[PDB]
Length: 110
Image (cartoon, rainbow, N blue to C red; front, side, top):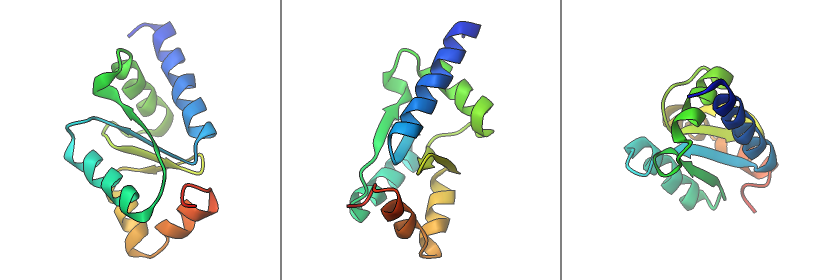
């Protein structure tokens, strides 16, 4: 991707994370991505999804996500503007009973 396209993906990704309480960067076929969204479905948490495989700039975004966060895989989950990580980081929050408080604090959960 071009210097321009990467910087554009970075600020498109950043504005998504800042403008939404729960953001998941994912791929329609990835299993950990589908697992994390169904859990959010079950908790009543509303999320905004970016299916990188369905976006022409999907690849520029994935590179920016690594620039920005240091993670190369999907899903990449942001809660309340902050980077949580992948399906495992999210599940670990839930195990400690802290996920639902976080999703409620930022409004993802009504």
